[PDB]
Length: 226
Ligand SMILES: [Ca+2]
Ligand SMILES: [Ca+2]
Image (cartoon, rainbow, N blue to C red; front, side, top):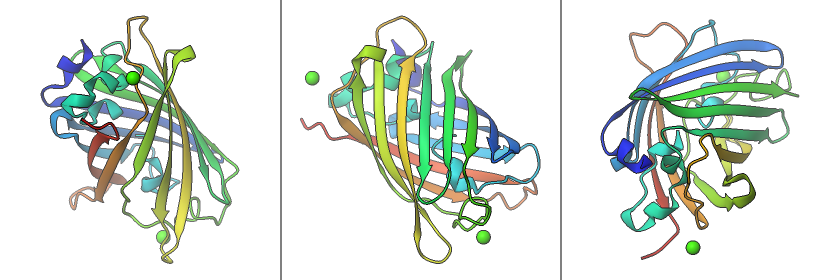
């Protein structure tokens, strides 16, 4: 059963290849997750030089199996139920009055390590918009991630609105639409409607000269009562 894989601290690896308006880049991340506490700690490095988009815009793309599901909601945890074989996670992310990301990721175990491998494609960005113009603050807001079953794909459909602070005090909306499908043919938990409540803190390693992001995140499932 997939839930038993997450009772302790699990090492995480993230690998992303991206192309945003023809700017090609790669990101590698390492850290660990402790789903008992809904906790993630990770450090990401841009391995190709300078990241051509703001780090915050990649947070959602860069492992919802580490969410804390309350005991009374554990029959609604799709993400862990798909493990260890994993799931495909696909998104379209529409940046208001700007371009979009489309992403396809596979999240699964490689031995004891939870791996997220992603291909990201961004098109229609404005050269001097908030994304390619690097006008977004280095911080991150707290969100609600809404989950429902998608029975005909044997998976889930997920929607939410990310709010990225702009350096002028305004907000850059990033509308997220997501689909997750299991990779194995084994049974998964197709959940009742509920949501995940997220919080993330971004920081820098004062000794790191590469372009990077340190992330501490807590996520708790909610919306189904005792
Ligand atoms: Ca700036
Ligand atoms: Ca039900």
